[PDB]
Length: 390
Length: 9
Ligand SMILES: [Cl-]
Image (tube, rainbow over all chains, first blue to last red; front, top):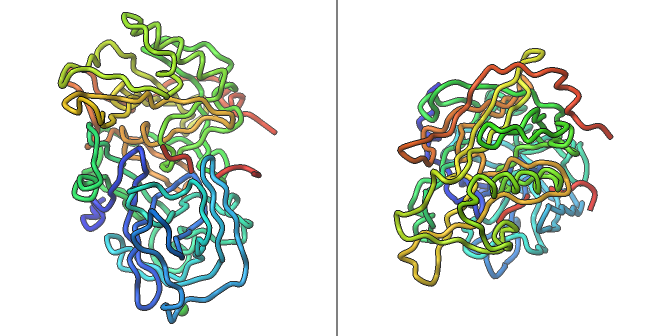
């Protein structure tokens, strides 16, 4: 696996999402697009907006075709509405192919675009079942795969800087790689461990076991996938269902309760600061997620460091310090393996064989002591029972 | 923070 053109083609930050550059229409207009495995709608700003430095102008694409249907997408936070249509799309640092795709011209947004986030659109990489207005609205990836020789698979290497990033610095830094139709061997170390996709809608997985420093949380594993568990590049934190959240937090407090912390810290509302270079990593637990594997009774695990679940943030005050926001949050809609998780791993969305691969990111953020890992195989029983059912 | 599509809304 060797796709040199697409290595380093993303930019961004776990806080505001990762984006790739695309083009649209004839002649073609360049837009930065947020990569989002947590939805299935390709949509772009098509009208001016405080935060947007540029936008899609249909009136200038000779190949644009209006579909005369409105759409409305509501995300976990933020929502928009637009008009549907099609036009020709390309990725400059992707494969040299052009593709007619459904595109939503976003005409009203609310809490959607981020100030100086640098992206102007969203690329929903998930499956048609969750496309709005309905599943007959074919997702971008589907079209790419149907109309060209690109294989039905892509991979993401989300890279964290290790420290806060400016807007200037985000633009100039490399934010990661999105390999389309492939796996690049140089972006990961160790081995790819695949988990099955439970159902083609979100990229849904089953978590069978959860460990903090190796200590099982001892829960009916059904609790970890209540009511789904998904991988999502457009979610900042690892988000967890209420029962599990409290249980997990408790455990971490215990593991590093050589320091009690502001209560608003855990609820993600406050920073924590240490002097430059003096961040006490070793005092913080590692988290392990065991994921249903390929064969019956077989699973594997992935392990994240505190470097993953404590987001670096710029302290406007002091600024010569090292500050973090706690990047694990509560959820009332199942588990979400957000970007904070993924920046540990090369992740492989093997749509063609209904499975998701994990490997250790060649670019991951680590200390001279521990390091993140993808280990297996483990033997767990009656895994199907961890799946939750409506 | 980003948090990308909802069920129903
Ligand atoms: Cl055409």
